Amino acid sequence: GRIAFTDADDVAILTYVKENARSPSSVTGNALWKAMEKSSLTQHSWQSLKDRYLKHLRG
Image 1: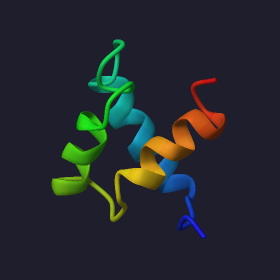
Image 2: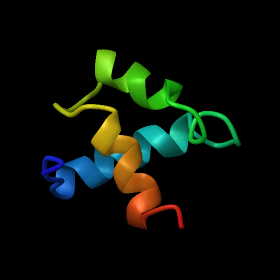
Image 3: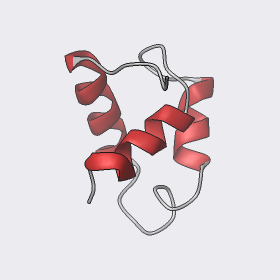
Image 4: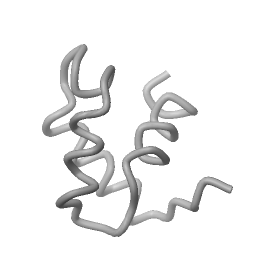
C-alpha cells in the first residue's frame, strides 16, 4: 500500500507543487519532492507525493 491522502494533503501538496513546481524540472526529477520530505508542512514522503501526481493529478 502507498499510504493514503486526505483533503489536507491535496491542499498542501498542491499549494507546494504549484508554488515551486512550475517547470520541466521540479516535477520531472525528485528534488522538489525529496526537499519537501525534509521540511514538509504535513507528514508524508516524497515517493507517494510524486507518484500520486503522475498517477491522476497533472495528467
